[PDB]
Image (cartoon, rainbow, N blue to C red; front, side, top):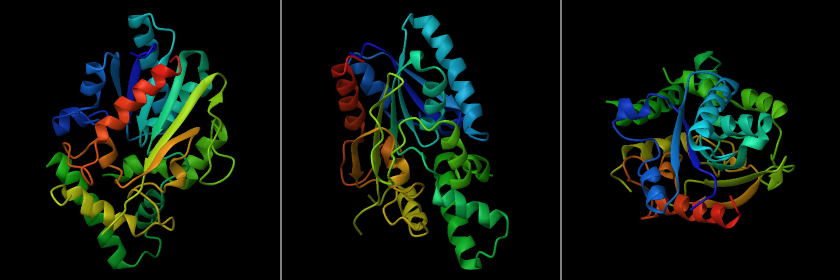
Length: 274
């Protein structure tokens, strides 16, 4: 068991209610089996990273009061790691670690393109259609207006965030950042789509989106290098953005045990006196 409780962090506050299961599919359940105290912070997707950061800090304050723990271990995905980074930067004595899993730490090329599409910025018709259809398929699969979530994840917006909260970012593109800054440990995981499975309709869509990145190694939403923060654990999983949280409902790539990435990392944290 970790010394400090684990807080799983993601954007999309309404996910569990709208979809009918957790964003981190089966993750909290497996972590608790291993004896860790686990909580989930589901943050507001349709606003800025700083707003999510503030929301997360309010969450953490209440949780520290309820647990009498002095710090938390953050495990964030996608939007999550940026909110985690805001909390660690402003309140480092309350944060034991930030673990980023496919975090949008340097911006999303797909969010960039989506913004050009919205601004009618000379995007050819055929590209507009491919991008929107892929996003439709992804949302439809979960559910049964997405610029709102991507607005805060463009390269321009995340560059501005990084300017304010530069802690643990790599000094060279695709490199590693410092493992410890202001006494907080930072770790990253990532993945990129590989190979030429079929039961998750989101994978085909993520592969459409993958083709529009200048960074060839990407998970459909974020380039491999953009994911980097602090010490690299592993980032060559053959998985898309959604696979890395064990979605949709456990349908992942290549029989990879996605849940095991999290439970092994929890033991790693415990080994670091976290």
